[PDB]
Image (cartoon, rainbow over the protein chains, first blue to last red):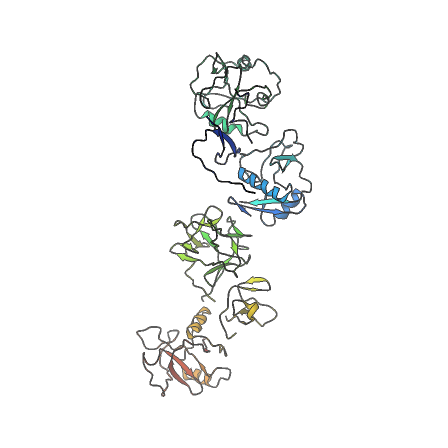
Length: 295
Length: 286
């Protein structure tokens, strides 16, 4: 369970010890970090051979449809499951595994499974979808693997559960959703790419401190398949700089002193703002570079 | 009159009132008295009328959960009122955390009744030989709080024991010469004040002579002649003039020591003997 955003994986050419990190109710709670383990940290779980987190849950083992289960357990003034927190998702998944079945979860869309939304009326802050080529209908279920399988819920599952409880800072951005296949010479084309659109248009450069939080809050809007963030740091003049002829002031390095001499690398932005650099040996990480990423 | 009435407990700062769910407490959804009803029952307990489930404190783990419990169990359930708050088991206040009630022993919380300034504790608890009823009680597998009417008895009937299933001793819901009902004079007075009436006040000889020939009456009972005020001699329940007395010649009638501070009426000859009325005996109050 190593999410490829905080660990550099390549041809590897002072001990190392890992740990689990929490980010105060983050959509990626449970990440695995690695550092030197000579320091002092905490340990809580040790492995040997219904109310939950200010919420209430009720499970029914009846085999009924989605509307039917809603009308069934709604008589007791209860609303179907709507996952909005990582701990709630983990508890729902462990309860489904203890019940040994895939139970109902409650939501509905409006226009051809394009705008998904819970029945509570809260802004989307959590996304744990399973696949991209599975969105055949406009409903979802929880599987064994703990993901969100996009299916039709006009069927009979062995149970149900229901619960109770852009211009910004003198710059304009843009998002491109197209399909591309150019996998060569990716260091002398982006400038002429954005310059053809309109004059006085340069690649995204960070000259402030509030733009990071702004683009972070803007990111989690269409993140069904988007999980990584790209940056404009590449091989420039035998150093790790931008594309334009301008020096760097805000350092975006993780730790130590990187010495990447390759023609390109992966400068990534984390979930909370951890500066991350990943040296790549295969070019099969470009999905994720130009099709459904931030350009 | 002075009797217990169903009410609702609401928070002062936030417009939230208590709503029970299968085993816990939920958000307000208030201003509708079709389901949310609470009342006071013996041993200083709170009882829900519709759900028939009472609340208690089960101190067993590090974090004591405030769930629902059965009113017939060893749950040690009772609640009292502090100057502007509620404290339960051991200085444990019903703290609110925006939807659920827990016990964190915080000194910043207020609780009032529905749409009126009151500490919801100014009215004290109000309630087979005419013994007082026991509320609540489990009959037919369900909890009941009031003397309901059925087709078995004439009118309302209640239980006179904590466990009616093992004792099977019922009684009449007393809301008047109650013969064979031996109670204490203080108990008789508090029960007749619960009904809003007062003890017998004899003003003329006509009523007394009418009571002499009465057949359906005990030969020995109380009248209510007692000195609740320690600085005056003898008064009645209400403020009636003292002009008619029927004292006894046999006893020397010691004022305070040697005798007692209560009166007992003998109707076979019409005398008023000095005695202590702390024991059980029939009575009559108008």
